[PDB]
Image: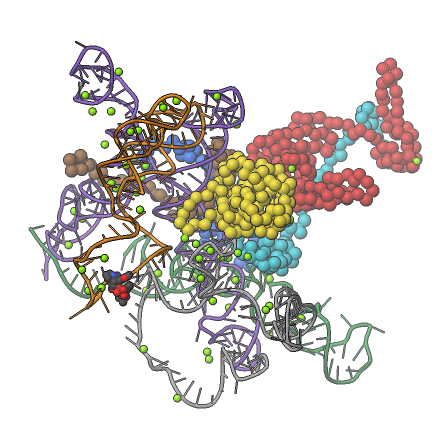
Chain colours: A red, B yellow, C cyan, D blue, E brown, G orange, H purple, I green
Amino acid sequence: MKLNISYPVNGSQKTFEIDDEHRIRVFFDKRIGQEVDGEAVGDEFKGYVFKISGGNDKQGFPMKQGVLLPTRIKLLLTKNVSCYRPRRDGERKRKSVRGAIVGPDLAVLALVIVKKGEQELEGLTDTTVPKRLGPKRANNIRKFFGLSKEDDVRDFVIRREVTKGEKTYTKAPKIQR
Amino acid sequence: SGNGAQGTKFRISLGLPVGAIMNCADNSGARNLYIIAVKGSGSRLNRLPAASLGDMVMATVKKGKPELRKKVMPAIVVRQAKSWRRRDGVFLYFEDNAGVIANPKGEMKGSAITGPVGKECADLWPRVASNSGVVV
Amino acid sequence: MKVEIDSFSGAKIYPGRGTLFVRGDSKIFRFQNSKSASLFKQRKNPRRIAWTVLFRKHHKKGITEEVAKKRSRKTVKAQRPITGASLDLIKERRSLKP
Amino acid sequence: KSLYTNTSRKALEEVSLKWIDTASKFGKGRFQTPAEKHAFMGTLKKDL
Amino acid sequence: AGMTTIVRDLDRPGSKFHKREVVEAVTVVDTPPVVVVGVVGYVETPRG
RNA sequence: GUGAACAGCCUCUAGUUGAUAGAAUAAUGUAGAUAAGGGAAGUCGGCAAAAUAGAUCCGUAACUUCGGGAUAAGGAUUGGC
RNA sequence: GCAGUCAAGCGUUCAUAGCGACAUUGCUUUUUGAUUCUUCGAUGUCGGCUCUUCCUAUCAUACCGAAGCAGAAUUCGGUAA
RNA sequence: GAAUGUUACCGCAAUAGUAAUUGAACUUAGUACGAGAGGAACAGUUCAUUCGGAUAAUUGGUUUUUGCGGCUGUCUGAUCAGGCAUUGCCGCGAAGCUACCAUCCGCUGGAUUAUGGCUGAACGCCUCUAAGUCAGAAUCCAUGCUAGAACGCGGUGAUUUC
RNA sequence: UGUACAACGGGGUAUUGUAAGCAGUAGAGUAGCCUUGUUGUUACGAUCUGCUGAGAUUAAGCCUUUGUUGUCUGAUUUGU
Ligand SMILES: COC(=O)C[C@](O)(CCCC(C)(C)O)C(=O)O[C@@H]1C(OC)=C[C@]23CCCN2CCc2cc4c(cc2[C@H]13)OCO4
Ligand SMILES: [Mg+2]
Ligand SMILES: [Mg+2]
Ligand SMILES: [Mg+2]
Ligand SMILES: [Mg+2]
Ligand SMILES: [Mg+2]
Ligand SMILES: [Mg+2]
Ligand SMILES: [Mg+2]
Ligand SMILES: [Mg+2]
Ligand SMILES: [Mg+2]
Ligand SMILES: [Mg+2]
Ligand SMILES: [Mg+2]
Ligand SMILES: [Mg+2]
Ligand SMILES: [Mg+2]
Ligand SMILES: [Mg+2]
Ligand SMILES: [Mg+2]
Ligand SMILES: [Mg+2]
Ligand SMILES: [Mg+2]
Ligand SMILES: [Mg+2]
Ligand SMILES: [Mg+2]
Ligand SMILES: [Mg+2]
Ligand SMILES: [Mg+2]
Ligand SMILES: [Mg+2]
Ligand SMILES: [Mg+2]
Ligand SMILES: [Mg+2]
Ligand SMILES: [Mg+2]
Ligand SMILES: [Mg+2]
Ligand SMILES: [Mg+2]
Ligand SMILES: [Mg+2]
Ligand SMILES: [Mg+2]
Ligand SMILES: [Mg+2]
Ligand SMILES: [Mg+2]
Ligand SMILES: [Mg+2]
Ligand SMILES: [Mg+2]
Ligand SMILES: [Mg+2]
Ligand SMILES: [Mg+2]
Ligand SMILES: [Mg+2]
Ligand SMILES: [Mg+2]
Ligand SMILES: [Mg+2]
Ligand SMILES: [Mg+2]
Ligand SMILES: [Mg+2]
Ligand SMILES: [Mg+2]
Ligand SMILES: [Mg+2]
Ligand SMILES: [Mg+2]
Ligand SMILES: [Mg+2]
Ligand SMILES: [Mg+2]
Ligand SMILES: [Mg+2]
Ligand SMILES: [Mg+2]
Ligand SMILES: [Mg+2]
Ligand SMILES: [Mg+2]
Ligand SMILES: [Mg+2]
Ligand SMILES: [Mg+2]
Ligand SMILES: [Mg+2]
Ligand SMILES: [Mg+2]
Ligand SMILES: [Mg+2]
Ligand SMILES: [Mg+2]
Ligand SMILES: [Mg+2]
Ligand SMILES: [Mg+2]
Ligand SMILES: [Mg+2]
């Protein structure tokens, strides 16, 4: 099955394919959340630790934290819940859901790194992707730089350059509160 | 089996011998089906012919639309109750006996099958495949 | 090769073993053996049958060290900053004061 | 040894087992190994 | 010795169970080494 | 005692413990039972066998000599404290 | 009851592919008759159930030959129980 | 099962019995043939029927395991633990037995019949036949399988002293 | 007279479904004495809970055993 891995430190992510029930089999009878030692899956990830966060079975239905079961069921879903986006106020819709217990019927595991193993992984530890947006509300700037209500934000706001072709520009948020 | 049956059926335990009455589980008008024969079955002094999942029987309707009564038609067994074994090693059984009325070509007479359906039957007859909700 | 569980008792059903009941509404019940199966036909309620997983779960039996603490967490702290905004002049201006 | 060289297909097929039942045969066996049984059962009034 | 169960993928191109698992029954015969203690030489006669 | 009860089942008083005996538990029997799925297809014929059953309450058709048919049919309920 | 020989006919034409009149030779002994030899100091009468075995004048199945056998289907005949 | 010296082990094989059966689907192929309507088969494969011989991992049936639990009635002052009710009744129930109600297995050489042939005279020609001969069937004989002749047999072991 | 055999005992395997005993602030409730209760107290109550997947049974044609205890020459017959 395909593994979809994330390094939530660097914002990095890359997918890996694994064909070998034995290597896979570590993930079986494991729930979402449960941690997993690396070497069992590959020599690459040795002493890497994996958190199981979800994934989609074949036919693409998603998992749902804490159903338990390693199958599918048809839950009633609401506002503010996984695997569903209401189309209308107070709308609820019955929908098939994959369990949160990993079977070999999954198309994809979704995983998140928690400890870094002994070796670097190419598109993950090596590369780092910047956070897209910066602090916009007053005291959030004051806490991304630690400032006290003295230092005055206005000059501590982020500043994102950009080019018009021959006119390079400058645009900062709009501090609120 | 015979006509319209594309595929081979692996032997499955025989549940419905002649005289068995099964639930009619389509929407043609018929409430039950009375088995009078089982297509493609053989002979032994005193042995009653018996049908199983995905067998074509010959039936009459005992309870149902008067248009469907007093006459003999083909029908197909879709649910069993007498447990049988599959090759993956499981012994399973339905809660009722049910067939659906059909023509020699194995095409249904009704536009839907009400209840679950046996895979061994779904595999065997396309239009029984078509009209199915839950299979097996 | 999947191992199933007993929908009445909750015991592992290794392959080709016990029996399978397809109810009229197409809910599928599996039994490890004829014992679960008869209680089940007998409309017995697993939660009241003392030797069942489902019973034991509900009466909180034996569980003990599952409610015992663990050790799973991390410690990161790596800044990326903000895309297009010179992630270099975001740490030298991030020298703080209080 | 066989007295003829069967070509069959059925003979010739080279099996390789996947799992061998090893559960008790003195009753409705539920457990492959004592390991498995301790695993599932938990701790008992004998035991440690 | 006795019997048990086996699970294995079937390889019969043509069969509805090609590349599917099957469960099949098996016997086991206890088979320690046999030990050689003599040779006996037969001859052909018109009596057999 | 239980129960409508001189019923059946258990007991007190009294009376018995008489009926050749031992070892095995093959076939076929005699008598007593159970059996998946089907449900009279068996058979001259449902022969045999199985099903039903007490009570309290609800409900009860044709037809009739008006007396019945009627426990018609069909239902629910029932321990212990 | 079953099978022949002759061949006038039938079969668009063409006796004999398949049939076959008028005649005529046979076989068979699950028909029914004719007989009265055995049993009247007694050989248990019909049908079914069960079960074995035999016959072949073969319904199916193996391999053939023929056709008024294009194919498909059929029909006739052989070795065949 | 007496007797062929005794006893034991391992074998031979006379004679006798003998077994497998039928179907469909796929593919061939919408092919051959046919104006068309229609419409095959051999090779390959997957299942099936009827029959047989076993077997009991599994599933099911059986229950005096009177094994565990439950229930009525009564009897042992109560409790505990029991008795009786032609096995009191009920749910589960191991083991054994057991079912196309369950699983597994059912061999391949030869010789022939019909029939189609080769060569080929009788009969300078012609002919499958007369001599000689090829191919050939759910047949037959073997192979295989079951008995083993208690008056068929072989090899081998050990063979008694108060 | 020995990886001998047997009777028990122990361990496994299995079947049932939680033993007896004690305890409880569980229990529809109920009585009895007063010092008439700012839990009054002593008991009683089908049933429930805990010790307790406990207890019981498990070769009579299950498996196994470093323990315990015991057994180990009676009878008849056979020769080319
Ligand atoms: C008309 O029927 C009878 O006569 C019957 C019977 O009585 C047979 C009954 C005999 C006992 C009493 C022994 O059952 C009798 O005398 O049988 C004779 C008889 O009785 C023993 C034997 C006979 C004559 C030779 C064999 N045969 C068979 C039985 C029988 C049956 C009949 C029959 C005569 C026989 C005789 O006529 C019609 O069907
Ligand atoms: Mg604002
Ligand atoms: Mg309906
Ligand atoms: Mg009959
Ligand atoms: Mg449709
Ligand atoms: Mg059972
Ligand atoms: Mg049962
Ligand atoms: Mg007297
Ligand atoms: Mg007497
Ligand atoms: Mg029955
Ligand atoms: Mg009925
Ligand atoms: Mg009848
Ligand atoms: Mg009827
Ligand atoms: Mg009849
Ligand atoms: Mg009559
Ligand atoms: Mg009649
Ligand atoms: Mg009667
Ligand atoms: Mg009954
Ligand atoms: Mg009347
Ligand atoms: Mg009436
Ligand atoms: Mg009440
Ligand atoms: Mg003439
Ligand atoms: Mg002509
Ligand atoms: Mg003419
Ligand atoms: Mg006649
Ligand atoms: Mg006379
Ligand atoms: Mg006469
Ligand atoms: Mg007479
Ligand atoms: Mg006489
Ligand atoms: Mg006689
Ligand atoms: Mg003959
Ligand atoms: Mg003949
Ligand atoms: Mg012509
Ligand atoms: Mg011929
Ligand atoms: Mg014959
Ligand atoms: Mg003969
Ligand atoms: Mg002797
Ligand atoms: Mg086609
Ligand atoms: Mg034409
Ligand atoms: Mg059993
Ligand atoms: Mg009891
Ligand atoms: Mg007490
Ligand atoms: Mg008494
Ligand atoms: Mg009595
Ligand atoms: Mg059989
Ligand atoms: Mg020969
Ligand atoms: Mg020639
Ligand atoms: Mg010839
Ligand atoms: Mg010749
Ligand atoms: Mg000649
Ligand atoms: Mg043959
Ligand atoms: Mg051979
Ligand atoms: Mg053989
Ligand atoms: Mg002999
Ligand atoms: Mg000898
Ligand atoms: Mg407990
Ligand atoms: Mg015995
Ligand atoms: Mg000890
Ligand atoms: Mg002793």
Residue drawn at x 88%, y 20% as measured from the top left = A169
Nearest the viewer among B94 and B57 is B57
Residue A130 rendering spot, x and y as whole percentages: 77, 27
Residue D5 rendering spot, x and y as whole percentages: 34, 32
Q: Quarter for ligand 56?
A: bottom right
Residue D35 rendering spot, x and y as whole percentages: 52, 48
Figure quadrant of residue A43: top right
- Kindly tell me whether residue A96 is visible in this rendering: yes
Residue drawn at x 73%, y 32% as measured from the top left = A9
Residue E46 placement, left or right of A44:
left
- Check the image and report above or below for A10 versus E25: above
Figure quadrant of residue A85: top right
- Kindly tell me whether residue B119 is visible in this rendering: no
Residue I65 placement, left or right of A146:
left
Residue drawn at x 52%, y 44% as measured from the top left = B57
Nearest the viewer among C62 and H118 is H118
Quadrant of image for the C terminus of chain B: top right
Residue C49 placement, left or right of E4:
right
Count of numbered tags: 0
